[PDB]
Length: 448
Ligand SMILES: O=c1ccn([C@@H]2O[C@H](COP(=O)(O)OP(=O)(O)O[C@H]3OC[C@@H](O)[C@H](O)[C@H]3O)[C@@H](O)[C@H]2O)c(=O)[nH]1
Image 1: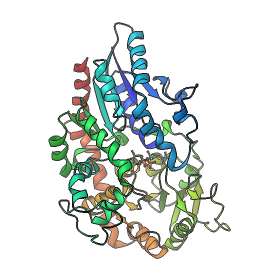
Image 2: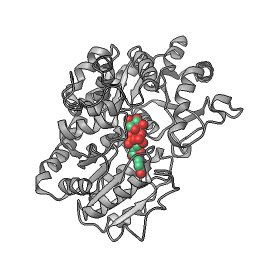
Image 3: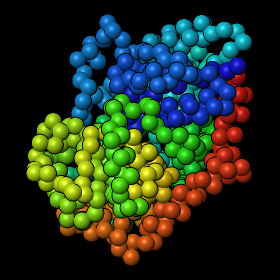
Image 4: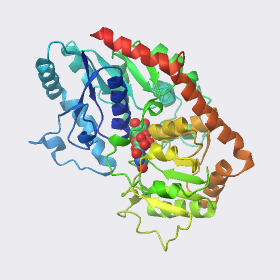
């Protein structure tokens, strides 16, 4: 009997992939222990089959995180804080857990978010193998390792170098526009992106939340840059991240979706972290109204700057085919037959979820890996359209309509339907994802 310890980054788009992986691994016969901060903790009563151990965040709270808040662009400062100061606590806790293990039981390995690059020299010190879980796409990692050339071509200078915004250099997928968006706040990113890449290269294995036919162009880079084995597993095809939600689900939404004709409803959701200037939020609203299609729109409270949920929204300005909710079980909704399209912020989990449900997309982005996910899905796969010039109602309403109603967008809908079938075929015996999971499980069993 073998135990796996998993250590997520405590944000929605990080615990979701990592707890899906833990359920999958638990299905292959492993014991699961999850290490978590108290901050942003999942409902552990939804995981009766997991052991939960809360660390680094506890109750005589250290002063670097003691006053750090819980909302907005800022709570993420715990990732650098914990990377630079958490090693000794992580080592005691791993030592305690190994010491407390029954002897018919062995810790096969540690799996952490790639962002926890500090975990690598901790696991080494304990002669424990660490595997990395990547929460964004092989394609964006190819951009990360391409960064030395980007900076030297003048691409990440947002001020002094502008206005050469089309086809980019050793990377014809993207426009220069997309590289500047991706790395806008530059040297916060490069230290973590540096140390993260350096220590996943040093890990014992990298698990990618993806499937081979989704990013086949990018495989050779990952094989050539990372000596550690790589495994491509599409987690949304295995299970939803539903029970690792950190907000309560509406689920009244399903009685209303049951009243829509098939493929007639646009799902709108801009992630778990994004915020928008009220001026922008009412232009998004009017684009939905001008589109003339039914929409179900998740507006997470705080989304709007600065209001507490939608107080700028008028009469029911929306309504008679529009609905606003605070939070849904997103993938379950994408799977309901009423949903014909998904307007996303191009977060990698949402994007993969929609790909795995066969829903074409409209792409907006808020930076980081998002504009490259958006360009990749919209121009290489061509499973949606990309609104790359900001918020304008007209251009919003034509994007929605072209994906959902226009004959001209039928190839985009067909692409989405086919991409899904490729994800399901990869899961069957002899498929790319199936063989990765079989390799990963046998690999983890040999580390023991
Ligand atoms: O209403 C909702 C909206 C969203 N969600 C879930 O929230 C998760 C959001 O993850 P996303 O990747 O879409 O995006 P987030 O912006 O929230 O954060 C993510 O950004 C991109 C990923 O690369 C990063 O790893 C993560 O930061 C999805 O798994 C989605 O299913 C819901 O369950 N309900």
